[PDB]
Amino acid sequence: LVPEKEKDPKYWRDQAQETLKYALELQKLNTNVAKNVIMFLGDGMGVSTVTAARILKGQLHHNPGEETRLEMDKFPFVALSKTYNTNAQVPDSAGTATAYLCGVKANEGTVGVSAATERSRCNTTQGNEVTSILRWAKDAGKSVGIVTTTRVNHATPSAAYAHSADRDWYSDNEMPPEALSQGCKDIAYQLMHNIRDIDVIMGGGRKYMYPKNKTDVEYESDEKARGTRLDGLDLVDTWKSFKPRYKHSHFIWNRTELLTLDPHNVDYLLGLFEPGDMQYELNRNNVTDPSLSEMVVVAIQILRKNPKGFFLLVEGGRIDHGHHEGKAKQALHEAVEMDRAIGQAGSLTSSEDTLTVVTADHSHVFTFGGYTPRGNSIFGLAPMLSDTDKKPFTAILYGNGPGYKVVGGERENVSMVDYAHNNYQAQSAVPLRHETHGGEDVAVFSKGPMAHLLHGVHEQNYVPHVMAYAACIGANLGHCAP
Amino acid sequence: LVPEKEKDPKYWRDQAQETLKYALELQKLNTNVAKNVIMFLGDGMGVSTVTAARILKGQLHHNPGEETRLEMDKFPFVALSKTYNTNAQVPDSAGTATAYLCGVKANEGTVGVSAATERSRCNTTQGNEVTSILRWAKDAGKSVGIVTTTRVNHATPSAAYAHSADRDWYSDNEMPPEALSQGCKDIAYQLMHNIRDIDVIMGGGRKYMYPKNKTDVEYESDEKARGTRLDGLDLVDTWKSFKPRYKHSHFIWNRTELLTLDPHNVDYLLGLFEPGDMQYELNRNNVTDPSLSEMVVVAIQILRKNPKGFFLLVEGGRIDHGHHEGKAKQALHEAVEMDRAIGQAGSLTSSEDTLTVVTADHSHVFTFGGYTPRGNSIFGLAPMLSDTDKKPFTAILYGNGPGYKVVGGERENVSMVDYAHNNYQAQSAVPLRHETHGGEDVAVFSKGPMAHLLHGVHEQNYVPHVMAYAACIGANLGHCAP
Amino acid sequence: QVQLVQSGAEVKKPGASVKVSCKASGYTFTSYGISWVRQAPGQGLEWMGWISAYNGNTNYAQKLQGRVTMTTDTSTSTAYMELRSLRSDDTAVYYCARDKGWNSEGSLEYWGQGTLVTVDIVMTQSPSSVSASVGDRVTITCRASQGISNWLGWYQQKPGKAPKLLIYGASSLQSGVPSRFSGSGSGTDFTLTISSLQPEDFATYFCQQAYSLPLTFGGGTKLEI
Amino acid sequence: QVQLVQSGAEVKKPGASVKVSCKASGYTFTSYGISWVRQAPGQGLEWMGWISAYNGNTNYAQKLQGRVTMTTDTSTSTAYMELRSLRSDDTAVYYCARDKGWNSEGSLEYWGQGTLVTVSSDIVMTQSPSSVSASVGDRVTITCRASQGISNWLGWYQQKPGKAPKLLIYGASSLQSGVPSRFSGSGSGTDFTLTISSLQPEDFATYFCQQAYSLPLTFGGGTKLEI
Ligand SMILES: *[C@@H]1O[C@H](CO)[C@@H](O[C@@H]2O[C@H](CO)[C@@H](O)[C@H](O)[C@H]2NC(C)=O)[C@H](O)[C@H]1NC(C)=O
Ligand SMILES: *[C@@H]1O[C@H](CO)[C@@H](O[C@@H]2O[C@H](CO)[C@@H](O)[C@H](O)[C@H]2NC(C)=O)[C@H](O)[C@H]1NC(C)=O
Ligand SMILES: *[C@@H]1O[C@H](CO)[C@@H](O[C@@H]2O[C@H](CO)[C@@H](O)[C@H](O)[C@H]2NC(C)=O)[C@H](O)[C@H]1NC(C)=O
Ligand SMILES: *[C@@H]1O[C@H](CO)[C@@H](O[C@@H]2O[C@H](CO)[C@@H](O)[C@H](O)[C@H]2NC(C)=O)[C@H](O)[C@H]1NC(C)=O
Ligand SMILES: *[C@@H]1O[C@H](CO)[C@@H](O)[C@H](O)[C@H]1NC(C)=O
Ligand SMILES: *[C@@H]1O[C@H](CO)[C@@H](O)[C@H](O)[C@H]1NC(C)=O
Ligand SMILES: *[C@@H]1O[C@H](CO)[C@@H](O)[C@H](O)[C@H]1NC(C)=O
Ligand SMILES: *[C@@H]1O[C@H](CO)[C@@H](O)[C@H](O)[C@H]1NC(C)=O
Ligand SMILES: [Ca+2]
Ligand SMILES: [Ca+2]
Ligand SMILES: [Mg+2]
Ligand SMILES: [Mg+2]
Ligand SMILES: [Zn+2]
Ligand SMILES: [Zn+2]
Ligand SMILES: [Zn+2]
């Protein structure tokens, strides 16, 4: 494409000099106390995903896209994190979530416990629990908040309040009778019972809070949207009954109410907008379901009232599902939505007393390449045909997954199908039903006070040990000691 | 598999606290003048390659390998570089080399010129030439060294001394008559007739320096190792004509002569060890071929004599050739050798007045990960069979390349063949003759004086300018101003 | 440090009004509210209301409504409480107390010196009076008429001194208190345990709930020697 | 800055040795070598040798070998020449000069104030013309030719009457820092050119071309640019 303005060396020299001047002025370190901490988390957002999301965001506004900047690319400090588990070489969701939320690496499939426990065994989790950064923040007088686009009792958010030996125990319906006999409790019970004064909770998973065979308010005729609890306890009713009678609790469940509320008269909020996982960004309903940006804005406005500060945990957790199913368009669109939410949240707060950290838990086997020309659509074909079987191939490819297609001995001719659709699955090397994770290191972006302590290549469990250092919470209180 | 010492949370907490203490002590910025500059360059070394190399290096010493640290992982500061060209979305070698060696982004396929020149056209080169950092170092009185495992006139090294409109013009034999008729020179001629005071040269490409049909020295009977110049000009002979008669010039061509020199009695050194590209690390010979570590050590010992500093450019460019063929073992072993060379060079010099920068120019579509257990061999099978066709699959997979095998209508059954061989090609999704590049951002590791100016996610051409600022050379001399 | 100071003793006659002032120093005045507590001679603590120093919203007890007014002045950082139509049973010690934080206004952390003036969820405490020797272990139980979750606080009062906060939330120890004291229980039954007894730990203990207005204090357990 | 100072005049007698001292200040003494140049009254520059201040290795001209001794003392940072068996044609002006850097040891950058001593297969460098005349504001060019190919090792010096020579261009294409950009140099191999595009009243002097290819170092015959 080669725009005219880029044909002069002076343009690049001036750009580099301006970048140098900014980086030289940045030498003044910020040694304030992080009054507020915000942690953005993208499930399965490696480096290739970030680059593809940047290109897509640029091209959505009729640009080549390569030169554009994401809202997380303006974060001054960048580091790399190793994501291996104690038990596994390729990471998982629960173990990594424990690593970067509690500060201690653990096995796979176990939430909120150390590495001395064994998966799916109740009588080995006693005395091996670990407390997450949410508990440290709440014990210091700060507010706590959880915003997710997935279930509130999914692995990534539940690693902050739950101590369970299995991540598949969503409710007592999924727990085997042996675990019930030995006294274990499902994740929803711990969500409503472990920390009894969590201010803002937002996400899906509305069918794990109701007794069995209870019709849903939103979907009347859907048989999969009914309740699943075998106790007979209404968990939302319990949640409304654990708070002082002179305060306000709402339990909104759609977008009209979320827009109607004013944060100046709300103290506790519980939003369950979907029976299970919230819908994709491209499949979302405008009228009845809110986006991540609106939920983040309302949560920030509610939590901003505390003079001691707040700790907000935001998850863009549909990237992992979009990659697992094998569709790249969806996952890139939730990456773009996550970036928009980051920008909206950063607009409200001030960088002088707020530590913002964007991170990921692992990466996938997503790849893109093939000598594509400048300005080429990221979902388009490669410029040259294959030189072995004489067929076109797309730029986006997967190491494995359900995209592996072979029609009678030869791979699929891409020109016969609509590769620009919303539900198109790119071709892969080995056929599977779900594309696996990846062992690559992940990138951690950070800005705010004491954000320069994330510099080199380090372990994952180092992330929650520096934030607690900046806010004078946890076990190390030497930042603001005399 | 879950070592005992890792079963206790105190271990991880103490590790994190020690890391935090080191990061706190690191707050004392280093603002000295970088007398020496060393630039390590891994061709096609992305973010999956470096972690795979770390695992392989750990496992070579009978360890799980995930926790082991490479010599480049001890570098305090890490940044990210965007690697797009002004003509292509997916980068190349020549354009990126121009970007990070001259400070100006250029077209795809042209070395040393700006973006205003068209490929394979010599009359657009005039007036559009750009000088690299090597000229800036030489004009300040510093020493100059180029050490490569590929040809000395390959794209990556030639982007520092040559201004040509095509990469494929290695010699006048390879240039079209129309280009020769216009007074346009090749790269081998420009290596000797552009900077006549390059101190140390190490690499291959001995058949581009001799007249046509001239027998080689190592390979007498090989007809592929003969000379290629149609001009009849002996470039090795004319290299020992532009230097003072009271100096010392040697022209060694094997390892026995290299490990017999006295660096206190050598001023100019040229080493051409192979007719073309130097052999792989697994295929290297004991006696008549030196490794990268020995060459780097000798080059540093020779360049260390200058009381004004030196600039050394080390290029481990066989990783790209290993990846292009689909052989992961060769590429990973080349990366390990590059890391060993980095360690040796760091041992020789001192970090108080030397700026060491390890970087890469692009990345490939290499991926690995199949939910492999801890301690699993990086070249081993995945724990579970495929869900669809019930066949084993390896952990290492390529997006596209020559590894795509389908025998009769079904993909290859890996359990039949020797998947641990030196020349085994992993399976891929698209059948091609050569594995392509990738559009991912690359990682830049930095250490030394003023090494903290590479902090965020930036462009590639920003890299040289910082060095020119740290060494007080080039167009920005504001570091030495009183 | 944080310190609250009140005026001197005031003697009045029935019908006349009385004003009590409380000046606080050591913190940002608008960030915390002020509660007013009453203690009759020989009986337990009684609650009148509080006022927030940020927005000025006030809450008064139902028993004393129509006679208590509360004002705040952030310019001089003072809180005033005025009572009207004094009766023969209004003689008592009035305390100004400060809450702990944002959402914890049921836990009175810092207390005033106490001004002497001369003219629902029922909380039960057991035992009425317990006697023990030095170094022993004692346990005191507090029961609520309704489920109050984990909203409970334990206070200690030595004779002639203001109450001191020991445990808030029935399981969390206040900073500056020895780890010897322990609190446990939840729902309807709560317990406070002292593993080792010392000569400086003989006083009267109260349990107060922060679930629903009005705030109710326990009857008091006299831990004698 | 860097400055070199010598001793006074030496009125000698034939057969008596003479010692010349040169003290340098403003830089690290051991990092640079010291060369010695001679100029007869009214004739061109002549080279005697140099000595390295780091390792003490010395090079002497073959014509004057067996009579010149060069010593260095890093404690007081001085360089000494001793000359023996003085002849009737040894009266001249002796200069101590400092090289430019590590490998640019044939380019004499800083020069001494000159000591006037009164007694009782080499590459031949040709320079043309000899007595060129011009006026203010004009453009002039001077050519220098070597007997052998010397690559780009050539330097251009300017000397006014009664003053030490000054380095202008080194490498035949690089302008020395502080020199006005009016002067230009070009050429490689055998023939080289030095050009002044706009002449100035303060640029009337004698110009020399000196090669740094092989020992002994040879100076040009000199071109007298008169007004
Ligand atoms: C969003 O949720 C609110 C719940 O408060 C819905 O309001 C109810 O709507 C039903 C209509 O079937 C009425 O019968 C109820 O009386 C309403 N409740 C209240 C408190 O107003 C609202 O309709 C929902 N929005 C949408 C678009 O469905
Ligand atoms: C893959 O599909 C394309 C699109 O149909 C094929 O290209 C067609 O080839 C037929 C051969 O007779 C032509 O008549 C059509 O005009 C072509 N269409 C286009 C759009 O090019 C292509 O041949 C297919 N690949 C293979 C290997 O058969
Ligand atoms: C390394 O290169 C040197 C070149 O200098 C080789 O030395 C030559 O060896 C041959 C053997 O036939 C002799 O005829 C030459 O006279 C040697 N030359 C010199 C200058 O000594 C040396 O043999 C090479 N090493 C190996 C292992 O082949
Ligand atoms: C892929 O190859 C493996 C062996 O390399 C096959 O496994 C063997 O199958 C034979 C068939 O009778 C058995 O007798 C052996 O016991 C199996 N195991 C081994 C270790 O040889 C496997 O069946 C092949 N895949 C398919 C789909 O046939
Ligand atoms: C847990 O229970 C199982 C079965 O009841 C038993 O085999 C196991 O030993 C128990 N765990 C421990 C630590 O004893
Ligand atoms: C929903 O909102 C999107 C963007 O806000 C808009 O493009 C679309 O037209 C709206 N309606 C439907 C039915 O998607
Ligand atoms: C430059 O060279 C090309 C051939 O490569 C020729 O077509 C073109 O006319 C030339 N341009 C000029 C200005 O001579
Ligand atoms: C020499 O080469 C052999 C293989 O030919 C290899 O095993 C060995 O490691 C090499 N080095 C030495 C010192 O033997
Ligand atoms: Ca909904
Ligand atoms: Ca060889
Ligand atoms: Mg998740
Ligand atoms: Mg290369
Ligand atoms: Zn994940
Ligand atoms: Zn996943
Ligand atoms: Zn390549």
Image (cartoon, coloured by chain):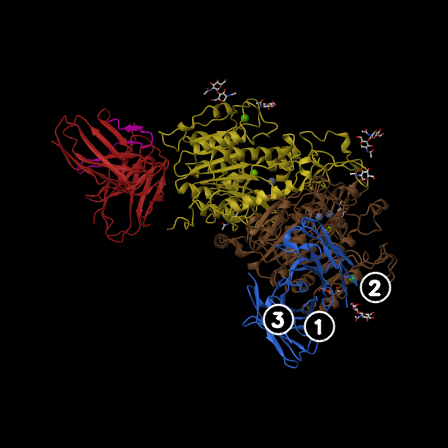
Chain colours: A brown, B yellow, C blue, D red
Circle 1 residues within 10 Å: few <14, some 14–19, many ≥20: some
Which dot marks residue A217? 2
Tag 3–tag 2 contact (CB < 8 Å): no
Pointers 3 and 1 within a single chain: yes
Quadrant assignment for the N terminus of chain B:
top right
Which mark is in front, 3 or 1? 3
Instruction: Report if residue A475 lies within the magenta region.
Output: no
Q: Which residue is mark 3?
A: C116
Question: In the image, is residue B107 above or below residue A144?
Answer: above
Circle 3 residues within 10 Å: few <14, some 14–19, many ≥20: some
Pointers 2 and 1 within a single chain: no
Q: Which residue is mark 1?
A: C61
Chain letter for the residue marked with disc 1 in the picture: C
Q: Secondary structure at mark 2?
A: loop
Which amino acid lies under the numbered mark 3 shown in the image of this protein?
A: Leu
Q: Is residue B358 left or right of residue A393?
A: left
Chain letter for the residue marked with disc 3 in the picture: C
Q: Position of residue A52 (x, y in %)?
A: 65, 51
Residue A325 in view in this figure: yes
User: Is ligand 1 less than 8 Å from the beta carbon at label 2?
Assistant: no
Tell me the residue at 14%/25% (across/down). D15
Where are the magenta residues, as a range? D38-63
Who is closer to the viewer here, C154 or D34? C154
Q: Is residue B432 left or right of residue D222?
A: right
Instruction: Report if residue D44 lies within the magenta region.
Output: yes
Which amino acid lies under the numbered mark 1 shown in the image of this protein?
A: Ala
Which dot marks residue B411? none
